[PDB]
Image 1 (cartoon, rainbow, N blue to C red):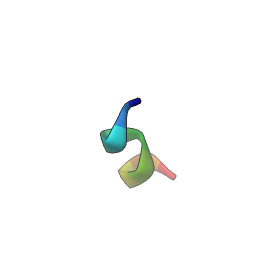
Image 2 (image 1 turned 30 degrees about the vertical axis):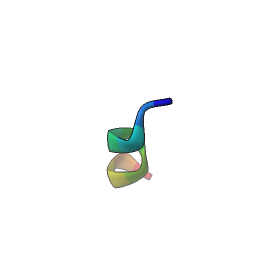
Image 3 (image 1 turned 30 degrees about the horizontal axis):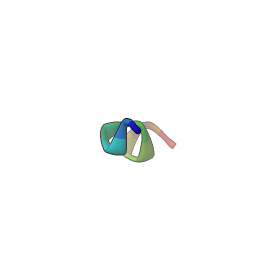
Image 4 (image 1 turned 90 degrees about the vertical axis):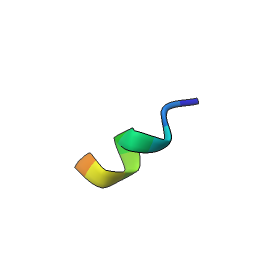
Length: 9
């Protein structure tokens, strides 16, 4: 749900 989480990956 959190597309921003991908940046953290």
